[PDB]
Image (tube, rainbow, N blue to C red; front, side, top):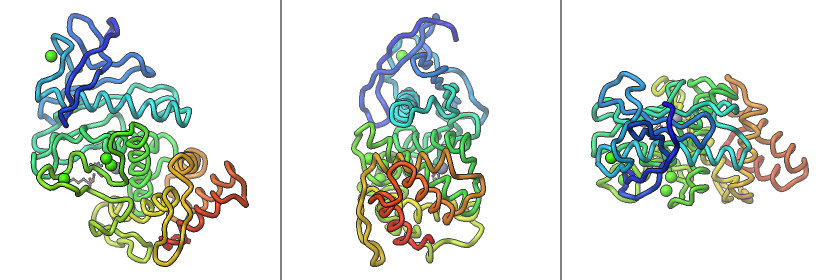
Length: 316
Ligand SMILES: N[C@@H](CCCC[NH3+])C(=O)O
Ligand SMILES: [Ca+2]
Ligand SMILES: [Ca+2]
Ligand SMILES: [Ca+2]
Ligand SMILES: [Ca+2]
Ligand SMILES: [Zn+2]
């Protein structure tokens, strides 16, 4: 809507207070005019029809329990926008400041979040497996990164290419979590997963096998569930990314870590310059090697550590 930009305040899913950019026109809308062509957050009102209604609030204060998922979806969309702008010089997910739209309160008891090709969609969870998914910055950044991927490499959501797609979203979801310095870790979804159980998460990049996901190519899933294991076999790439960043010895192969910043620069370059819709793990290796070569030189430590990491997870 057309109106005057302002700043509201609310509480997110985890009970934390934050300021959010809003727009005033009779109501205060969750419409952030300060980032690209806008960040818009919608109420899906527990239905599956999208996007729903642009979130309208009478007083610019968002402390109602119903408000919490919208505050975080709106806020963390902004953070993710900031990350891509400031770190990678990318304007929104299409590189041309496309409006970012999110809908919360999608369906009833819905334990997922997704980028549907036009917008982000967040369920509220069933209260036991998940709480509202937008409360996880790595979730929001995971989904918004699918938008980046779909606009750039275009990795299809099947088989190894889909696992790369999912891994990229976990990687950048984690890099955004670190960028926001909000209890950062190499776990995915810990903030909104199983409120009854502390210390777990949906996926682990540091040790994917913690939750039965593969951490070596020899353990990759070859069946047809999950579009050929796109959320399963991502663990192989997540581990490699984790090793590039943090280093370590994995199945007897030692990796000198080069840090998060360089991991992000390498994978962003691989994503936007070298990967294609049907890239597989081996091509991801080549793309990451070439990106590190581009940025740091063929004889650099960075290239060596990328090689070592993929060697460690069995991706030749
Ligand atoms: N986003 C992943 C994991 C979430 C599972 C929620 N039931 C998937 O769709 O499989
Ligand atoms: Ca209000
Ligand atoms: Ca965390
Ligand atoms: Ca995390
Ligand atoms: Ca938990
Ligand atoms: Zn995903």
